[PDB]
Structures are given as C-alpha cells and as structure tokens.
Length: 330
Ligand SMILES: O=C1c2cc(-c3ccnc(NC4CCOCC4)n3)cn2CCN1[C@H](CO)c1cccc(Cl)c1
Image 1 (cartoon, rainbow, N blue to C red):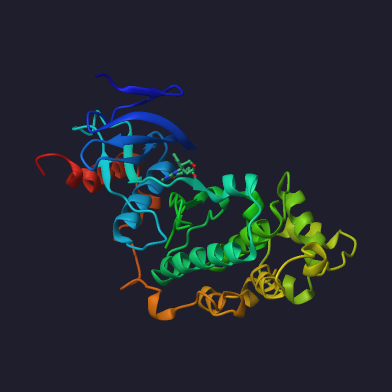
Image 2 (cartoon, rainbow, N blue to C red; image 1 turned 90 degrees about the vertical axis):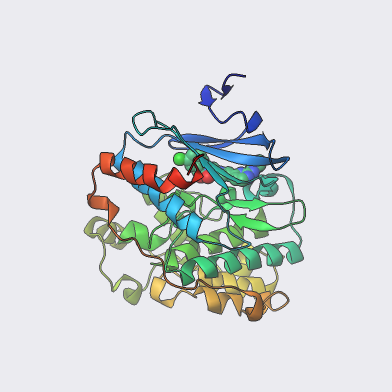
C-alpha cells in the first residue's frame, strides 16, 4: 500500500505503521495516531520537517538527544525513529512515541476537576519536572496541551522541541529580561485547573504584562531591581498603580493550601519563586509526596558541540547520524 495522507501531510511510515489519524501539530509538523503491527498497539507518530531552518534543526537534534537519554514515568519517550535511507532524500523525520488518550487542554475544556484530581495532576507534573530540572534541562513550553493523560489519570510531559540545558504561560522575566520559568508555567496551569480558564490570557506582549499586573499588583522596586529591557521598564513605570488581588478572591472555592502554593509559584521575582523540590514538599501535595519514589537524573545533561554555531547542513548530518541506530541493518 502507498503512503497515507492526513490533512495534506503525507506520512511515509508503512508498512509497520498504518491506519493513521490526526492527533496534533506544530510549527513544522503534524502528529498522528497509527497502528503498530509489530507490538499490536496504537502509537503516536510525530512528523517533523525542520531542515530548511537552522533553528528547527537545532530543536530537532536537542529533542531527540534529550528524549533518548531521559527515562521517566512522567516524561514522553522515543520508541522508534523513521527517516529516509540517504541524507539527500531525508526531508522529514518521524518520531514514534507511546500513544496517550488525551491532554489536559481537552480535559479542561470539558470536565470540572475535583481537588483530589488537581492535586494528583499537579504532583505528576512536578515529579516529571523534578527529573527534568535535575538533569539541568529546562522544558520552556509547559502548557495544558503538552500535558498528556491516560484513562487511568497517568500524566506525561511531551514536546521537548524547545528544551535547553506560549504567551499565556510565559514568565514575566522572559518578557522583561533559568529553571524558574518552568515553575511559573506550572503555576499558570494550576490556576487553570482551579477555574477551567487561563489565568493570564493576554492578546499580545503588553497585554500579557497587564494581565499579570492586574492580579499580582504593581511590581516593587526590588522586583524591578534587576537587569531589564529599557522599553519594558519605561512602560511599567508609565502605568498607574495596580492593587494586588488576593488569591482566595479569584478562586473562592479553592483549597487554601493549593492557593498558598500557587502564590509561591506565581511570584513575580524569579529569585523568590519556589523551586521544584520545595513545591513537591508543600503541604498541598502531602498525600502524594514520596521522595523515595521520585527519580532524578544520574548526571546533568550537556551537549558536546554547541549547535547554535553550526550551519543547518551540518545539523542535518548530526540528525542523520543520531537516527541511524533505528535503521534496519544497523
Ligand atoms: O509533540 C507534540 C505532541 C505529541 C503529542 C502526543 C503524543 C502521544 N500521544 C498523544 N495523544 C493525543 C491523543 C488526542 O488528544 C491529545 C493527546 N499525543 C501531542 N503533541 C502536541 C503537539 N506536539 C508538538 C507541538 O507542541 C509538535 C507536534 C508536531 C510537530 C512539531 Cl514541530 C511540534
């Protein structure tokens, strides 16, 4: 049988993988579910076509190298990689992953979560994040659609395309000026689990800052005592005073312990923001916290070359090399 086509994208993954169905997409690719006739289960297949852009080639190599090294229950892995037999023919790379049922984005569109579920989901996000940060890696795009879920409420973090050694979930430092950006994102996700709506839904950069200030209040002098973009600093100083809104006013029915943790994750100053181990140890997560059952990385991850300097043609070679061991006859 020929290759299958899904929403205009051809998927050349047969004969092992067939009966394909759309399940997601990104800047330079598409994800489908597919039947694996070897393991006799359905899998996820992520198609990416990065080779025309140096940045996308960088991201592709990082994502593959990081996910091939990582091993953790709350982190998506790589089971297989398909690409053409020669580098001149390789225009696409197919990354095969465990198939999950849904994501937190879809869940929050349709279901009201109980405190217990919120607690358990938050715990697994942070358990996975502890492993990532222990490897000295930042995810940088945590958000509900990148948190995958099973029938049995198991949670896995996916999409490590932006990982290194989305506006609504973007930490203020990023816009004004480290691991703390991931904590901010988790805080945004916690808030969204509590209310089923994004806490800071800005329409653009300035609007994002305005929503954050609308809740946290005007930043203090120490909050601004840092290296900071001149334009952003002048903008913030041009604004009238904004009062802080108490968390319990915004989330009237929330567990007070959840709101205490939320306060510490959504702290404006990254240096005062709670870190992942301290968050796991917060009273809100007491029911699930189990440091004897929370694996960390054996060593910190680092790249041998640095890829930012490499031409995209050289990056392609490295990707071709990295993926070779999944080829038949290897
Ligand atoms: O990497 C992923 C990804 C993998 C999965 C995945 C993996 C395993 N299972 C399920 N099940 C699904 C079943 C239906 O409900 C949703 C969960 N989904 C979902 N996404 C979200 C999009 N991306 C990123 C962009 O963030 C991406 C994708 C393609 C190209 C690029 Cl450049 C980037």
